[PDB]
Amino acid sequence: SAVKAARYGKDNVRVYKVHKDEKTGVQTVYEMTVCVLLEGEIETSYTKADNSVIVATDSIKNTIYITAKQNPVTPPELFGSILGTHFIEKYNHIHAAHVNIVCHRWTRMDIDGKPHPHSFIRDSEEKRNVQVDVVEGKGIDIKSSLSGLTVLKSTNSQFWGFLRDEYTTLKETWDRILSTDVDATWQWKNFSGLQEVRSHVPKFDATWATAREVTLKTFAEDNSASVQATMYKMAEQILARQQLIETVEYSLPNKHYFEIDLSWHKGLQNTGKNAEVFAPQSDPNGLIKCTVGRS
Amino acid sequence: SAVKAARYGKDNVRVYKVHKDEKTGVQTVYEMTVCVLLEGEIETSYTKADNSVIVATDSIKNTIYITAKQNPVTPPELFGSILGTHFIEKYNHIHAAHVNIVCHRWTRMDIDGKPHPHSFIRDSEEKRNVQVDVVEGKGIDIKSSLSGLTVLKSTNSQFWGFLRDEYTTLKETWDRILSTDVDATWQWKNFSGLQEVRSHVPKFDATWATAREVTLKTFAEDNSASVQATMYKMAEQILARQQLIETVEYSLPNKHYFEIDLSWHKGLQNTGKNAEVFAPQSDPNGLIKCTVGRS
Amino acid sequence: SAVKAARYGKDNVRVYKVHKDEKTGVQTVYEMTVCVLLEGEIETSYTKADNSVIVATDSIKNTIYITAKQNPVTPPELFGSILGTHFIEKYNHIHAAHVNIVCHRWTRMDIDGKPHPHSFIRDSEEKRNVQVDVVEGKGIDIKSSLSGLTVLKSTNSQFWGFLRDEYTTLKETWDRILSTDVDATWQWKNFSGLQEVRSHVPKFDATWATAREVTLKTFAEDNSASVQATMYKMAEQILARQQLIETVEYSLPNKHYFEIDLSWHKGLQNTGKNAEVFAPQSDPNGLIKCTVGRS
Amino acid sequence: SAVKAARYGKDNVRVYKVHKDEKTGVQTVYEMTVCVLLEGEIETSYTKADNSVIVATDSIKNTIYITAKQNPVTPPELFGSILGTHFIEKYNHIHAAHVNIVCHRWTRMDIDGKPHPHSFIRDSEEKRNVQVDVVEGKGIDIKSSLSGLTVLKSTNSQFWGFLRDEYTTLKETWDRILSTDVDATWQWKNFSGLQEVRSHVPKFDATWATAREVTLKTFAEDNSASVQATMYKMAEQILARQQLIETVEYSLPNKHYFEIDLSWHKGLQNTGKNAEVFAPQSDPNGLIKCTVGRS
Ligand code: NA
Ligand code: NA
Ligand code: NA
Ligand code: NA
């Protein structure tokens, strides 16, 4: 036997950081969950009980906090790049660092119509994420994403013209509910190192904002022929608006809302044009995926 | 042996309803999870295999959908009152109906600064709930609540002057983070029946709004001596603003954010006035409760 | 306004304890999650920012660990009684302690047919719990329970003879699946204090074992007329086997498994006597409850 | 823009199946959650609203049930192979089927020391899984796994000799707790099609059993130098015992149990040799991974 692949580190590292402006009194908070996994010349820790090659996961945890103290934690693409670069530069025998960051929402409260200087609300479990893979000799590969963005439209979704055979029972429809949890990923051009990442820093927040905006507007305005067709429109627009993105990935569940036939009860009409009360289905669910790139 | 208490019914009944304005094109959606449990002269179903006294839970489910089709589902205090009244009036031998409703957020989207007619976002897992107990001969008892409202303030929380003995290690502080998940309940005066509930319908949305507003503003503005002291201020203000409320209950976790001493590393200063990076603690957590009533 | 009720403390306190037998090498582990909430002359902490009456929740946490170090943690009824007694005796102004313990399973592994001295498996998320309410001047009130015991029987469940009216669609059946998650509680006679609890210590593990055994055997052997009827049989037997129990409570979901009619496809027969493939339903679910006491 | 990758289908399809032996009365149950995602000449569903190429996800769901009715559902490697083969053979334009199955435990109950013919218990949330990728022209690729196997050993884990630098605070130890949730995967030699899978059917249950047995015995008996070293031993033994496995993957969290220094309280000794009460840490956690193959 032989080790074919190995990575190790610390997961579920919760981190908070505050910024305090001493002139204005305005405080700003950031909260994330971080995972760092390392690769390198570490196989003898597996095969020969050689712990000398192990940068302890406890030390990886310490390093996350120290790096957050000494550097900005925003945008997460930059923080992850700084963090991963540290491990491959500090340790000769570590050749890759894989950094995953989940950013949690703390939105400033408005109190009597005014932004409060130090109070925040978690307006949803929607996340902003990054996966930053720092590989010695091969730059920095960043995937940015939004996830847990849950939406519903009550009309202007259709599904007809699909294949019909002996396994098919689904009726065609020209007016249905469409609800999903959006998981959208934009994959950046490889960066040569930390200097190139830094050179693009404003584009990370701007591209996240674009991806979110395009998602919401396309979902709301597309009279959808299918989830497939709608998600492709989203991807095409994001690629048109940021040339440093190479691909856009969507993964969308179709969270079904079923009509309820009540005509057995006093002739109640609750289907078709008369449909008002629906049964949300927890499972099963459609799951639709695509990766869109440049033609 | 003998049955001392018994209730049964259908839980986790997911319900969606849409309202469509045919003049304006504007659609409005509601989504809830409903539980209905019945009590009455049902002990022989337990003791003698007498199913004749059982209104089947499947039929209770059907009834929830039928009632949603025939009545408004908002405010949930009214829907729950209609639903519970149905069971005790329809079935001579059923003497109480216990209706729990969890309302899920579907907030209308703004697209290019304009409200969209049929697209919605789940802006958080914060819930609006009701518990409506309809008891024959004893009216309708309603508890309304908000839950899952997650907040954080980065300063203007203190905790000093607590009891100190041989079990105490906690340092006094004059500046800490305070974060919680708000669970707030307002308990209404008993209503004699459905007519009295209907007579107060506008007060249900208005009192929910007040409770939410008071919670947020008091949390943001109170330089908190303790969770105890801050939550009491919230309750007192809600009682002052709605005379048909008899009591207000809060249940608040203290979701700790711990300082991280980094001075072992290059003399880094990250405590006290220099504290910037903190470790959010998943557990344990303080848990603080009170019920406030009229003096 | 005035405080009508108040309790506070530390929740989600995870605790592990090991016992090591230095003669045999055999180690035994216990793991729990503890909550302690206190009541007493504490209202001024809410109304007047008087923290002097607050035994800090951090100190409550410390006390849990200290008490686990100095006392047995098993049976949990005894540990909870020791812990709650400490708070009301130590602090003159604290008059009640409410202790909830969730015990997690660590079952010793058998390796090559032999019990291993120090290795354990979590054989299910089934829990053993206690609620111990220690109230000054009013003894110790204990509720013991098992929860998260998930079972299924594939036949020998029936449901016919229920009420049928214009809200009913459910077909009668003489052979269905029955699956539930058992939540069973046995409520002890009040104990006058810690000495009386200690005097009954062996009965706590023995009654838990009886409750579990009766649950499983009755579920497996009762050709069930209803969940109501089956759960009553369980309760009656537990009360017959431990005179120091005053009541037994069950709360049982009916986790439905629906037949799937496949006759639209090649005349496939999958209902009634031919039913082989079923659709487990995540929601909704029946929910059946009773409390049984002594006649 | 252009579609670079696309797959779609039905997720979270819950399936139950019963086998009834009409001679003996013995019933046997199986429960799974299935996901099927298809790939093929489907890009025009994304780019041109062409639903004619879509085998509806609802039809995929129907097909799962139909296939379970007509074929054995065990071992899951075989069921998944049958299911995936169906889609690529039935639909000329579908060229890959990706089938994920999670198998849920229903272990037969022993009642008064005897196996019951039709009653079962969920003895843990441990799962047995498969990922079966059926690719036209490229056979069938199967990954089998066990997951959610949660274990703890109270001694005979060590961690010393790791790298120590200015980021390190962790003390070396020669006696610690080790607890993990085992996720173990064995990757089979490619199979040319369904006939070859069928030719090996008994090896699927036997290899799962071996993987489980080796995991448990190695965890219990290895005086562990590190998680790395222990997991490698497990993998090497599984590869030695089944030549049709090409690689074994482990992913193991290190679920920390921290000592609690109580010496501030009455000189209580609870560290080192005196350590009895520990604080289980929910987060962060080490995360250790490797893939082991044949040298
Ligand atoms: Na390096
Ligand atoms: Na009645
Ligand atoms: Na006292
Ligand atoms: Na094909």
Image: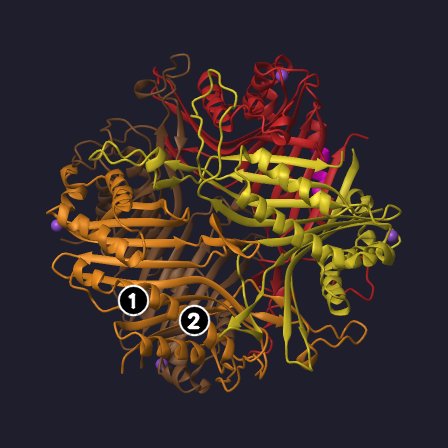
Chain colours: A brown, B red, C yellow, D orange
* Chain part drawn in magenta: B231-237
The residue carrying mark 2 has its beta carbon less than 8 Å from ligand 1:
no
- Helix, strand or loop at disc 2? helix
Residue position for label 1: D203
Of A242 and D55, the residue lying toward us = D55
Q: CA distance from mark 1 to mark 2?
A: 15 Å
What secondary structure prevails in the magenta region? Answer: helix
Q: Which amino acid type corresponds to the residue marked 1 in the rendered image?
A: Lys
In reply to whether residue A274 is colored magenta, the answer given is no
Residue position for label 2: D213
How far across and down, in percent of the image, does residue A102 sit? 43, 57
Identify the residue at horizontal 47%, vertical 71% (top origin). D216
Q: Which amino acid type corresponds to the residue marked 2 in the rendered image?
A: Glu
Identify the residue at horizontal 71%, vertical 62% (top origin). C74
Where does the N terminus of chain B fall, quadrant-wise? top right
Visible residue check, residue D41: no
Whether residue D40 is situated above or below residue A130 in the rendered picture:
above
Q: Chain of mark 1?
A: D
Few, some or many residues within 10 Å of mark 1 (<14, 14–19, 20+): some
Whether residue D85 is situated above or below residue B50 in the rendered picture:
below
- Helix, strand or loop at disc 1? helix
How far across and down, in percent of the image, does residue B238 sit? 68, 31
